[PDB]
Structure formats: C-alpha cells, structure tokens
Amino acid sequence: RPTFYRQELNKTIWEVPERYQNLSPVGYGSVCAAFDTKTGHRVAVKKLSRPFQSIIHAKRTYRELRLLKHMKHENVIGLLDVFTPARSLEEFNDVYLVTHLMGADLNNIVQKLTDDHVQFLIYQILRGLKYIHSADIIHRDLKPSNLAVNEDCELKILDFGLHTDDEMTGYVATRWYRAPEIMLNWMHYNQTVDIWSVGCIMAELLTGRTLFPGTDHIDQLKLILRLVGTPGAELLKKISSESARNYIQSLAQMPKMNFANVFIGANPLAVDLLEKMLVLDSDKRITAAQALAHAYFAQYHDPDDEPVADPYDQSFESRDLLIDEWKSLTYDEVISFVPPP
Ligand SMILES: [NH3+]Cc1ccccc1N1CCC(CO)CC1
Ligand SMILES: [NH3+]Cc1ccccc1N1CCC(CO)CC1
Ligand SMILES: [Cl-]
Ligand SMILES: [Cl-]
Ligand SMILES: [Cl-]
Ligand SMILES: [Cl-]
Ligand SMILES: [Cl-]
Ligand SMILES: [Cl-]
Ligand SMILES: [Mg+2]
C-alpha cells in the first residue's frame, strides 16, 4: 500500500498516493490534472461524487469501473490506475480513477482538413469501434466532444454512455448525433446506433457544418427524413409503438436525396461510405468491421492490425443486489487492479 497525503482543493478533500504531484483542478465527480512521477505522464485524476448513495448510483459506479478495466486498445481510453485511501471494506467510501490527460477534442480541430485527414480520423474511430463492438458493448454517446485528438492526428474514443430528459431537449449537440430509433424510442436498439453517429461526424468533417442540427426532436426527425427518405413498410413493421407508427404515416412521403448533390465536391468514395452508414433501417447499416474494408480507407487498412477484444461478461446487469453488495463488488475490483506495462 502506498503512502497517501491529504489536501483541500476548491472545497473538496483529495487523499491520493505520493506518486501523484502538483494537483490542479480542471472541472458525477471532480477532476484534477496531475503529474504521475511513476510513469512520467500527465494524468487526469477523477474523484467520484457520492458513488454509493443509492442502489442505482452504486450499480453505475461498478459498471463504469468494470468497463474501464476492460478497455485495452490504441483508439480507446484505458485505465492507468484506480485507488481508495480506505484500509478495509468497512471504511470504504471514496473511489478515484486515473487516465491519460487529454488536450484537444475533435471540436478544437473541426482547422483546414484535407480528405487525407478525414480518412485517417474516421479510420481510427472505426478501428476502435470494431474492438468495442466485438465485446458486445455499445458506446451510445459518440460525438466530437467525446473524441480526443493530439498534434499527430491520433484519436481516442472516451466518455462511454453509462443522459436525462432535460439534457436532450431543444437545440442541443447532445442529441444531434443520435440515431432516430433511439431518439424517439422506436424499438430496442443495438450497436448499429454507433455507426449512425460516425456518419454524422464524418459529414461534419467534410463540410464544416452540423449534419442534423434540429431545434427539437421533431424538427430533427424532419431534417433526417428529408435526406434519407421516409420509411417503407418493411421498417414500419419493426417500430413497436402504434402511436409512433401512426405519427410516421401522417408525414408525406419523400424519396432519398442524391448524396453527391449534398456533399458537393467530396471524394466519391467518401460519398459512397456515407450512403452506407446513414441508412434509416438499422438492420441494413454497414458494420464497423465491414467499413474498415471499404475502399475509402485503402491507404490505412491493415487486417492484421485491427484487433478484437477479450470476451466481456455483462451478466451483472440483470442482477438485483443491495447497496452494500454492489459496494463490496466494487471494492474487490479496486484492489485486484493490475496496471499496464
Ligand atoms: N461548407 C458546406 C459544404 C461543404 C462541402 C459540401 C457541401 C457543403 N454544404 C452542406 C450543406 C448544404 C445545404 O444542404 C450546402 C453545402
Ligand atoms: N444541416 C445542413 C447540412 C449540413 C451539411 C451537410 C448536409 C446538410 N443538409 C442536411 C439536411 C438535409 C435535409 O435535411 C439537406 C442537407
Ligand atoms: Cl505513491
Ligand atoms: Cl489511454
Ligand atoms: Cl475511502
Ligand atoms: Cl459535441
Ligand atoms: Cl404523401
Ligand atoms: Cl469479463
Ligand atoms: Mg464528454
């Protein structure tokens, strides 16, 4: 067990191992930047706020720790350390998570981007997604502010979806990248919702403009259906709510637009890929593994260097436990953590 030291920074007590120095507040928890003297990296240290206050919060704390401990891929955020100052389960109350400190996100770039930049950035998102989806994990919240990018144009996916009603209302970027079947609760969704988000991000890199900046859910749906067309009978059969089906059928029918006349002057191979991502019926969207083999990425695709994940057991999600049982499971995962090389 390392030696810990305590200090108050901006109304909160931080008790951390000596290896972490020069803590500086930066921003579910509070975050400080710090220098990790054991590894030489600048890191983000997050102190979770009230991690075990309710059953829902205790289970969410466990879910986040299990997910971050599993993610080991060049294009996905990983866990550098996790610690508690508690010496026993009986006094266990606080959880601290340590990751690499991220500078710019895709917004702080979306600069002057060549087609070669768009190829490389979208390739890396799909490479990370192939890995995430191979573990039957759905990210659910892909958008430019959840993508870290450095000076060398290298990219990492972060901030997995572990959002409320008010957060999704009105003219808000939190909703502009969401697939329509989850925005309006049409059906049980699956990993294909993430590919819809990649399509929205790719279109924005190519044009410099948000693809579907709706002023509310309904305005956004109208923008979407004007581009991709209104649904046919095949998709309508898959929407569970009779009211939602009734609303769809109240709209005048529209054909799918010509994407070459929307994305004027774009690489024809980029146009072709966008048509395969932005498909209304989620069953028919291209998958991440299929998209990596698309000719738009010929310059970067290497099927021997696009790895999949170890199997991931999510059976805990259907388990009904008490607060102190979720807390003990979390404690076990903190003390069994093994750092990366
Ligand atoms: N700067 C915008 C841009 C760059 C490249 C290709 C298309 C576009 N616009 C996208 C929106 C279109 C309106 O529907 C107008 C053109
Ligand atoms: N929001 C404008 C925009 C920005 C970039 C690229 C395409 C677009 N439109 C998206 C909406 C489409 C109809 O809804 C028309 C084209
Ligand atoms: Cl230490
Ligand atoms: Cl990382
Ligand atoms: Cl504690
Ligand atoms: Cl964003
Ligand atoms: Cl009609
Ligand atoms: Cl597992
Ligand atoms: Mg975020």
Image: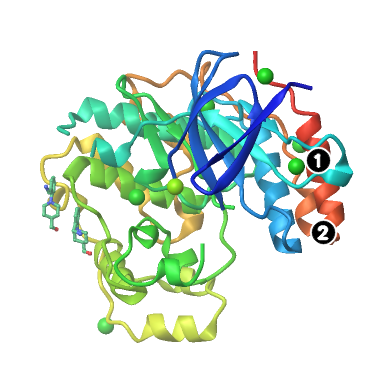
Q: CA distance from mark 1 to mark 2?
A: 12 Å
Indicate the secondary structure of the residue bearing disc 1.
helix
Q: Is residue 160 visible?
A: no
- Judging by the rendered image, the residue that carries numbered circle 2 is 323
- Judging by the rendered image, the residue that carries numbered circle 1 is 331
With respect to residue 302, does 31 lie above or below? below
Report x, y in % for residue 337.
Answer: 75, 28
Report x, y in % for residue 114.
Answer: 17, 29
Q: Residue at x 42, y 36 (%)?
A: 291
Amino acid on which the number 2 mark rests in the picture: Ile
In the shown orientation, is residue 15 left or right of residue 146?
right
Q: Quadrant of the N terminus?
A: top right
Indicate the secondary structure of the residue bearing disc 2.
helix
Residue 98, image quadrant: top right
Q: Residue at x 79, y 50 (%)?
A: 315
In the shown orientation, is residue 174 left or right of residue 38?
left
**Nearer to the camera, 235 or 8:** 8
Q: Quadrant of the C terminus?
A: top right
Amino acid on which the number 1 mark rests in the picture: Tyr
In the shown orientation, is residue 283 left or right of residue 53?
left
